[PDB]
Image (spheres, rainbow, N blue to C red):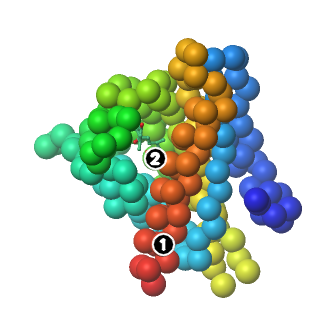
């Protein structure tokens, strides 16, 4: 996946936001997407907590309060497209750092099986031409009698598809 030069450059961010030391019954993974677009452009979409459906394929709609303010602790209600093993997710914004380009959220409830899910998404400048690397990591409980391996495959597949869609949206923005 990540090159040596990408790792090195990305080392302290990964230690700071994307490394976990967990007990059993919980699992994590880290995923990376390269985007051939300025990190200002990528971050302008990543940080828009009220409109995840701009890049998240499986989200049919997202509702926020009439008094919504973009501030740690604000919440959103997302509704999943039809036919899926989940219908809704209730999510809380945990991080919004406009200097470092760090965001994250937690799933506090809803109709789905990704209990105590929390993810962190970070945006990184690379200079070849300016490009961007996005890291996204999550921790989640392993539902009793499911395996850690199926849980990770599920989360990873959704995050990977979302970060691909992010890359296509943000590259089209040039
Ligand atoms: C597509 C989908 C299906 C589910 O079964 C769970 C949930 C409804 C939470 C989800 O929206 C999960 C989305 C997660 C993994 C990544 C995200 O959105 O950053």
Q: Is residue 81 left or right of residue 157?
A: left
**What's the mark number on residue 100?**
none
User: Who comes first in sequence, dot 2 or dot 1?
Assistant: 2
**What's the mark number on residue 96?**
2
Q: Nearer the viewer, residue 141 or 19?
A: 141
Q: Position of residue 161 (x, y in %)?
A: 51, 57
Q: Position of residue 99 (x, y in %)?
A: 54, 56
- At mark 1, the secondary structure is helix
Q: Label 2 neighbourhood size at 10 Å, few (<14), some (14-19), many (20+)?
A: many
Q: Label 1 neighbourhood size at 10 Å, few (<14), some (14-19), many (20+)?
A: some
Tell how many labels. Answer: 2
Indicate the quadrant of ligand 1 in the picture: top left
Q: Residue at x 34, y 61 (%)?
A: 54
Mark 1 lies on residue: 168
Is any atom of residue 74 visible in this view?
Answer: no
Is any atom of residue 109 visible in this view?
Answer: yes
Q: Residue at x 53, y 63 (%)?
A: 164
User: Does 134 appear above or below 150?
Assistant: below
Q: Residue at x 56, y 28 (%)?
A: 140
Q: Nearer the viewer, residue 49 or 71?
A: 49
Q: Position of residue 147 (x, y in %)?
A: 63, 24
Q: Position of residue 114 (x, y in %)?
A: 47, 29
**For the residues marked 2 and 1, what is the alpha-carbon distance in whole angstroms?**
23 Å
- At mark 2, the secondary structure is strand
């Amino acid at each position: 996946d990540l090159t040596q030069d990408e790792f090195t450059q990305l080392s302290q961010s990964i230690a700071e936001f994307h490394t976990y030391q967990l007990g059993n019954g919980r699992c994590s993974s880290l995923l990376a997407q390269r985007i051939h677009a300025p990190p200002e452009t990528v971050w302008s979409v990543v940080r828009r907590f009220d409109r995840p459906q701009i890049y998240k394929h499986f989200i049919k709609s997202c509702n926020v309060s009439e008094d919504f303010e973009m501030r740690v602790g604000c919440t959103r209600d997302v509704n999943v497209i039809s036919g899926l093993p989940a219908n809704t997710s209730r999510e809380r914004l945990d991080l919004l750092d406009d200097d470092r380009r760090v965001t994250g959220f937690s799933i506090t409830g809803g109709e789905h099986r990704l209990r105590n899910y929390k993810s962190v998404t970070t945006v990184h400048r690379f200079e070849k031409r300016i490009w961007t690397v996005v890291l996204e990591s999550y921790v989640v409980d392993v539902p009793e009698g499911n395996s850690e391996e199926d849980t990770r495959l599920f989360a990873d597949t959704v995050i990977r598809l979302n970060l691909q869609k992010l890359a296509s949206i943000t590259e089209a923005m040039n």
